[PDB]
Image: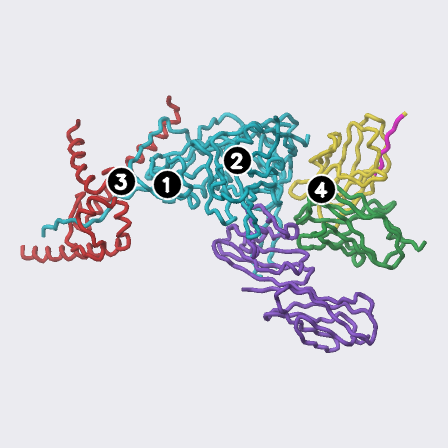
Chain colours: A yellow, B red, C cyan, D green, E purple
């Protein structure tokens, strides 16, 4: 299967600063040019939500702070500006072919005084 | 162009002679608009072409070079069972054409055969003179 | 005849509009001075449900859409011929998605050299019934290809009174069309939320007139409206296009009022919720379509409402009632409300007749 | 806006078979649902995907013979059935909606709250 | 007039057919003149009836004429005639539904009698042709009964039901 590896394992950011998370794949997933990646967020006590899809088109209701980029087997989810509410566990998923394979997840913690 | 639809057969036949007498007596541009002049001239040329071709091809039945001919095929009664005045004063042209639309294929063959017979007899006489 | 007619549009050829681009590539300017001949006492049987012109404009519009809104993903199926598991797999397609402006432009339809177009003049036309005051021309009036469902947008009005048209009433199978004689304003404005407003003071009168005209066919029963019965989102609720945005709007607060000879609606501004989309169901076949994200904001639309599409619900369980639900979606149905007059004809000169003379032989 | 809900938490004995339910309310027809599992230290992994509009089936290899899904669109409810219960089977379960056609997985605009299952004899 | 039999829990197909291959309109009307489905352009519109939610249709065969009508979670009361309206014809089919099962859910013993419950539509006379692993081919009409039920008779007896030359296979829950 297409094995996904996320980075960094742990991530810390000061409020108001850029945030970035990377996801890499063992095999290419390009099919007619559309990138089939989904970025989800998970908070304790609540189920995960779909935050970004396809790496090029935003989900409604989610503020515009999120964005995506990359190609091939290296993709990046970018957040700006970070806030107190964004401390959570983010997952990168491939939506190319079944069976599907989640990543390792990355933890974002808000850094304050 | 011989007449305006709706008018009866006899009225158009009567009025055509007067129309001929009258006609013989002699009594904001877009530079892409040039296309429309050609669109009109082509239509006129095609009309003239079709008129000439049809006039030339109307000669099989021996009625070439005329607009009102006559033939030598007797008129049956099973086709219309109608008299002169009713046909020539009523039954607008479209209705009459619809009425006898079933037999419009046999009459052509009958007329062609009659023309062939007349031509053969005339040539036989020509052999005499 | 069944010839091929050419387009005719007063295009511009300088702007970015895709309609302008298509008109410039293949259309020619309009006639500088039209000429209409008023024929006399003629009577020809007009039929609109069986016309052949629509089958051509509907294939021209689809070609037009292949130059304005290209799809990021065009997912359509295709099966393999097997008598019966018949092979059927989804096919993927993708191209560039550059955002472009979009606004319909009037288009004229004309006949080539050798044919004519008859047009009727009766104030009612009875639908598919013969009329007398006929005229002959070579081109039609201005037509806007605006696309929508459940409501007819900007378009020509009636002559003097709102009229109802249907192929065969009493069969609860064919869509009923209604044409008004005075347009009603509509204004839609707005990231994923927007509102639409319609003048109620005119809409109530419009419904009153429509119902008053309608009772004639069904005098005894009581006419009542009701919201859509369900189905695809493109037909349950109003859907249209504006500024490269595919607006979907619910229309429940307009058909809940049960109507009688009196008023039972209310007693300003009729608010109407709307939310844009990106994954839509195509109307040119089967398969979903996705486009690029929406524009930044500040998009407005002002339009007129002239026509209406209404369906009927019949059966033997009916007890002195008649429920009329909103429907539509068959683009041919939406477009027959504009080409129900013109008829293409060819002229035949020949003729055979029995005369009293005899040939000289 | 499509919404989903799930039943309450469950305590079960090992080796038995149990059925959980997920209720979705726009009604779902010709859609394509999946099931997801969450256990500590393992992220997420999708288990089974069925299509009610024809009851089409797609399984993950690791769960072969362990999970059976069903659906009843009359009550608009999908069902997860799992047998051969052990300690490792204690986890949270989620139901995920979408829309039809095979490899869509691009419009998961919502997810359920999830149901907890614990396999213990206490 | 093709006639089909249901199972009270499974789906069934009732296909019309054409030859133009151009996605021509159609419908599916019951015996009471009520719409259920029907193409409108290229969309779908369910009829305002009691089977709005369960109904469906295959949206890939519309390009090849076959306009089926897939019904999910079938029930007995749904037996009635249905009609296509492809172009101008009146292609119609009939469906009858009857649920055959066993009233004794799980409480069963050895040496007692077993009786089956059949819920057939009011106004039809299907014939239950039962079949058992031990060769117990009990033949009867709508109502059938068995006076013996023991260990040797384990397994869901394949007592089908046939009517008008068409038979549907059912099973009976047997636990002892």
- In the image as oriented, which residue stretches furthest toward the left? B129
Residue at which label 1 appears? C344
Image height check: is D122 above or below A41?
below
Q: What is the CA distance from the residue labelled 2 to the residue labelled 4?
A: 29 Å
Mark 1 and mark 4: Cα distance apart in space: 51 Å
Looking at the rendered image, the disc whose residue lies closer to the viewer, 4 or 3, is 3
The residue lying at 65 percent from left, 30 percent from top is: C194
Marks 2 and 3 on same chain: no
| Residue that numbered label 3 is attached to | B6
Q: Please tell me if label 1 and label 2 are on a single chain.
A: yes
Q: Residues within 10 Å of mark 4 (few under 14, many from 20)?
A: few
- Residue E41, compared with residue A78, is above or below; it is below
Prevailing secondary structure of the magenta residues: strand
Q: Mark 2 = which residue? A: C152
Query: Residue D2 — which label?
Result: 4
Viewer-proximal residue among E154 and D88 = E154
In the picture, the quarter occupied by the C terminus of chain E is bottom right
Q: Is residue D62 left or right of residue C311?
A: right
Where disc 1 sits, the SS reads strand
Could you tell which of marks 1 and 2 lies nearer the N-terminus? Answer: 2
The residue nearer to you, when weighing C211 against C16, is C211
Measured Cα–Cα span from mark 3 to mark 1: 19 Å
Residue at point 40% right, 39% down? C125
Have a look at marks 3 and 1 and say if they share a chain: no
Mark 4 → mark 3, Cα distance in angstroms: 66 Å
Along the horizontal axis of the image, is C285 left or right of B85? right
Q: Which element type, helix, strand or loop, lies under badge 2?
A: loop
- Image: magenta residue range: A106-112
């Amino acid at each position: 299967d297409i094995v996904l590896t996320q980075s960094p394992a742990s991530l810390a950011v000061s409020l108001g600063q850029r945030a970035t998370i990377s996801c890499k794949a063992s095999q290419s997933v390009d099919y007619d040019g559309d990138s089939y990646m989904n970025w989800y967020q998970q908070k304790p006590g609540q189920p995960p939500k779909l935050l970004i899809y396809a790496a090029s088109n935003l989900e409604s209701g989610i503020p515009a702070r999120f964005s995506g980029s990359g190609s091939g087997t290296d993709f990046t989810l970018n957040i700006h500006p970070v806030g107190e509410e964004d401390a959570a566990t983010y997952y990168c998923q491939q939506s190319h072919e079944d069976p599907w394979t989640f990543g390792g997840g990355t933890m974002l913690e808000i850094k304050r005084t | 162009f011989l007449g305006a639809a709706g008018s009866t057969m006899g009225a158009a036949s009567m009025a055509l002679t007067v129309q001929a007498r009258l006609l013989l007596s002699g009594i904001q541009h877009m530079l892409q608009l040039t296309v429309w002049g050609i669109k009109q001239l082509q239509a006129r040329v095609l009309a003239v072409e079709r008129y000439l071709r049809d006039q030339q091809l109307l000669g099989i039945w021996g009625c070439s070079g005329k607009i009102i001919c006559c033939t030598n095929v007797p008129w049956n009664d099973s086709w219309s069972n109608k008299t002169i005045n009713e046909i020539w004063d009523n039954m607008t042209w479209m209705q009459w054409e619809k009425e006898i639309d079933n037999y419009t294929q046999h009459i052509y063959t009958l007329l062609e055969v009659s023309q062939i017979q007349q031509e053969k007899n005339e040539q036989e006489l020509l052999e005499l003179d | 005849a069944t010839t091929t007619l050419f387009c005719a549009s007063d295009a511009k050829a300088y702007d970015t509009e895709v309609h302008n681009v298509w008109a410039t590539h293949a259309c020619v300017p309009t006639d500088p001075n039209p000429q209409e001949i008023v024929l006399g006492n003629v009577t020809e049987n007009f039929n609109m449900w069986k016309n052949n012109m629509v089958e051509q404009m509907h294939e021209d519009i689809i070609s037009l859409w292949d130059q304005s809104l290209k799809p990021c993903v065009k997912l359509t199926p295709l099966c393999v011929t097997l008598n019966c598991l018949i092979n059927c797999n989804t096919s993927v397609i993708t191209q560039a998605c550059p955002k472009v402006s979009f606004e319909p432009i009037p288009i004229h339809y004309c006949a080539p050299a050798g044919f004519a177009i008859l047009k009727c003049n009766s104030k009612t036309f009875n639908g598919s019934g013969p009329c007398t005051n006929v005229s002959t021309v070579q081109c039609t009036h201005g037509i806007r290809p605006v696309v929508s469902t459940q409501l007819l947008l900007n378009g020509s009005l009636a002559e003097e009174e709102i009229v109802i048209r249907s192929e065969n009433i009493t069969d609860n199978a064919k869509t009923i069309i209604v044409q008004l004689n005075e347009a009603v304003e509509i204004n839609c404005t707005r990231i994923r939320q927007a509102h639409c407003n319609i003048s109620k003071a005119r809409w109530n009168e419009t419904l009153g007139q429509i119902v008053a005209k309608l009772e004639e066919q069904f005098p005894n029963k009581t006419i009542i409206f009701n919201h859509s019965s369900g189905g695809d989102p493109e037909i349950v609720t109003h859907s249209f296009n504006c500024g490269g945005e595919f607006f979907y709007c619910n229309t429940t607060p307009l058909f809940n009022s049960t109507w009688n000879n009196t008023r039972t609606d209310d007693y300003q501004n009729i608010t109407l919720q709307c939310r844009i989309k990106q994954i839509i169901n195509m109307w040119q076949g089967v398969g979903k379509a996705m486009y690029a994200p929406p524009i930044r904001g500040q998009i407005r639309c002002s339009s007129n409402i002239t026509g209406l599409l209404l369906t009927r619900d019949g059966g033997r369980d009916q007890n002195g009632t008649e429920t009329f639900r909103p429907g539509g979606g068959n683009m041919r149905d939406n477009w027959r409300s504009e080409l129900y007059k013109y008829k293409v004809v060819k002229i035949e000169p020949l003729g055979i007749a029995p005369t009293a003379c005899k040939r000289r032989v | 806006q499509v919404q989903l809900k799930q039943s309450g938490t469950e305590l079960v004995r090992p080796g038995t078979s149990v059925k959980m339910s997920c209720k979705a309310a726009y009604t779902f027809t010709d859609y394509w649902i999946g099931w997801v599992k969450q256990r500590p230290g393992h992220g997420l992994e999708w288990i089974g995907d069925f299509y009610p509009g024809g009851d089409y089936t797609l399984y993950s290899e690791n769960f072969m013979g362990k999970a059976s899904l069903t659906a009843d669109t009359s009550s608009n409810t999908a069902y997860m059935q799992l047998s051969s219960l052990t300690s490792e089977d204690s986890a949270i379960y989620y139901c995920a909606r979408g829309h039809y056609y095979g490899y869509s997985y691009a419009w998961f605009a919502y997810w359920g709250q999830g149901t907890l299952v614990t396999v213990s004899s206490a | 007039k093709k006639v089909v039999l249901g199972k009270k829990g499974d789906t069934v197909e009732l296909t019309c057919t054409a030859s133009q291959k151009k996605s021509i309109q159609f419908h599916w009307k019951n015996s009471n003149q009520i719409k259920i489905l029907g193409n409108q352009g290229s969309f779908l519109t369910k009829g305002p009836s009691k089977l709005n939610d369960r109904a469906d249709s295959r949206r890939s065969l519309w390009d090849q004429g076959n306009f089926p009508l897939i019904i999910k979670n079938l029930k007995i009361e749904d037996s009635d005639t249905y009609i296509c309206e492809v172009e101008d014809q009146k292609e119609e089919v009939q469906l009858l539904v009857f649920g055959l099962t066993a009233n004794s859910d799980t409480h069963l013993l050895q040496g007692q009698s077993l009786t089956l419950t059949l819920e057939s539509p009011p106004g039809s006379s299907p014939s239950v042709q039962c079949r058992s692993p031990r060769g117990k081919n009990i033949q009867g009409g709508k109502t059938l009964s068995v006076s013996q039920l023991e260990l040797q008779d384990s397994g869901t007896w394949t007592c089908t039901v046939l009517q008008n030359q068409k038979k549907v296979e059912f099973k009976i829950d047997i636990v002892v």
